[PDB]
Image: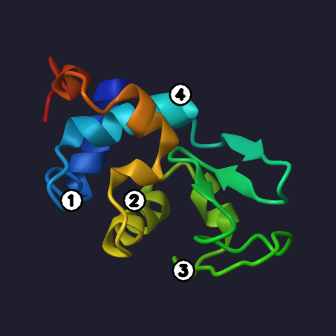
């Protein structure tokens, strides 16, 4: 599924992301936009043997198990295929874990390079909450 901006904002809000660990909703929407272009099926296969999965491009070395990645930690305790669903629940739950495991949103390269320092509120502006 390819989400709309406001639709994804609403879904993320329903799942508790607004102000999760001090990160406003627009940060999360921005991260998804630049990680996956809102596409729940996005995959990026890396040359290091890992793969980035889903709307938030969560990597298979630390976070989910795909059975093919060296050094797998599976800290979200899920198969990576769960991150490719049309429902965002698994991706949100794992994203929460990523920040709970001592990272901030700097874990997402696209957030650090394309969202940090910007008017992230723009990503939710005009939307029904």
**Which residue is located at x 59 percent, y 59 percent?**
83
Residue 55 percent across, percent down from the top left: 53, 44
Residue under circle 3? 75
Mark 2 neighbour class, 10 Å CA radius: few under 14, some 14 to 19, many 20 or more: many
Residue under circle 4? 37
Q: Quadrant of the N terminus?
A: top right
Whether the residues at callouts 4 and 3 have beta carbons within 8 Å, the answer is no
In the image, residue 75 sits, relative to residue 23, either above or below, namely below
N-term mark: 2 or 3: 3
Secondary structure under badge 3?
Answer: loop
Residue under circle 2? 92
Whether the residues at callouts 2 and 1 have beta carbons within 8 Å, the answer is yes
- Which of discs 1 and 3 lies nearer the camera? The answer is 3
- Total labels: the figure holds 4
| Mark-to-mark CA distance, 2 and 4 | 16 Å
**Which residue is located at x 58 percent, y 70 percent?**
63
In the image, taking residue 14 as reference, residue 36 lies left or right, namely right
- Which of discs 4 and 3 lies nearer the camera? The answer is 3
């Amino acid at each position: 599924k390819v989400f709309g901006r406001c639709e994804l904002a609403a879904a993320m809000k329903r799942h508790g992301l607004d102000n999760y660990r001090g990160y406003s909703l627009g940060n999360w929407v921005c991260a998804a936009k630049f990680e996956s272009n809102f596409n729940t099926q996005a995959t990026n296969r890396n040359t290091d043997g890992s793969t980035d999965y889903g709307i938030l491009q969560i990597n298979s070395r630390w976070w989910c198990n795909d059975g093919r990645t060296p050094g797998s930690r599976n800290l979200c305790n899920i198969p990576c295929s769960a991150l490719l669903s049309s429902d965002i629940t698994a991706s949100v739950n794992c994203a929460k874990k990523i920040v709970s495991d001592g990272n901030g949103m700097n874990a997402w390269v696209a957030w650090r390079n394309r969202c940090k320092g910007t008017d992230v509120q723009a990503w939710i502006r005009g939307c029904r909450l």
